[PDB]
Structures are given as C-alpha cells and as structure tokens.
Length: 229
Image 1 (cartoon, rainbow, N blue to C red):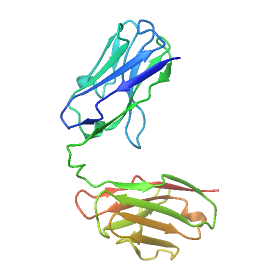
Image 2: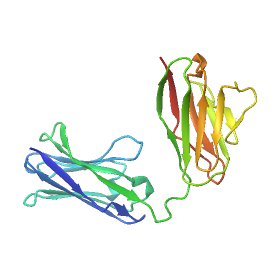
Image 3: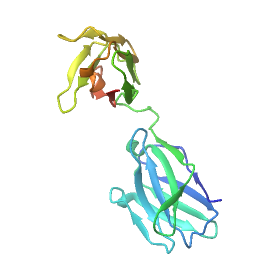
Image 4: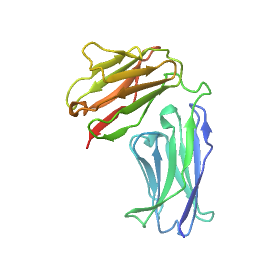
C-alpha cells in the first residue's frame, strides 16, 4: 500500500514561511519522484515543484524564488519550504508520488494551510452558491450570495448573456432594475442575499452574479452559470 501523509502548520501569519513534511511509505525515494501541488479554495490545481529519484529539483516558475524541496531517504520524508507567504497562498497542499519520472500516481491526504493576519481578511468576500445549475424551462431557481460582513442592502444582481455585457437585474438587494421582467426577484439584507428566478425562460441562459458596494473595494461573487435542459 502506497502512503503519503502531509504534516503542516495549518495557520501561518502573512510574511512568514511554510514548512510541510511528506511522510511516505510503500515506495522508495531513490526510485520515484515526489511533487508538491496546491489547491486554493474554488481555484484550479497548481503544481509547485518536484524532486526526482536522483535528487533533481524542478520548480514552477511562478514560485522559484521562494520554494525549496528537500528530502531524507532514511526517514522517508520530503520537505517543502515556501518563503514570504501571503493570503494568496491559502490552499490545500498535497504531496504526490510519481512512477519514477513519468506519471503522478498517488496523492496524499493533503494539509489545509490558511493564511490570515488574525483580522480575518479585509476586502469583503461575496460567496455565491451554486456555481452551476442545470434547469428545465419553467422551474424556479435560487442563487444566494453571502457576505463576510453586514453590507446592509448595498448589493446589485447582474445577468450576463454569453458574449455580451452584464446587465442589472436587481439593485439595492430587492428592487428590480428598469425593464426587468417581474419573474426576477431579490431578497436579503445584511449578510445573505437571494436572487430568485420564477418561470425560467430560454433567454435566461446566462451567467448571474452579485456585487457589494458597501465598502471599498467593490467585490463580486464568483458567478453562476444557468444551463437549460
């Protein structure tokens, strides 16, 4: 059984370093290489670097300056070290084992690394749910958007059809923009907000998103694509 388990701090303050330990078993560090991957919340997978069975270390150019990958074959451990950590580096960090040098075979449990000064973050994050939705014509669907702070009613809901510009659906949380069909409705005040579409029509196939305008900077929701069966 091939095993890899990450050991990491979990909480790191901005500008500090990061040292994660991949404790491996079931294979030989002399033969197989080990890579470091990270997954930010709601982002794609990001490859950091690799140490090969002979010791050759390659790094992703985006980090290069601040990455270090070492190991200890007697202890069966591979070490990652990153410098000048900031909020952007908040991600789930994995170590993965290759088949010698070709294909990345087996992943570890992953260790979650969160970077925050203690103020929890400062920009106000609008979290949308759901990111995707497959609907039938005539259903009623909800999209919600949650704020990390009371933004009162300073929330605007936009629709953006494919290859077009966004267009205001709801303004001030609950009021329909001019010329908006009465089937789009807005609810909410404070932290949670809800765009509701009754009687889903074919032209509703678009990308919907929220925006807060309580405090700078203005921040949008990640978006929501509406597909129709």
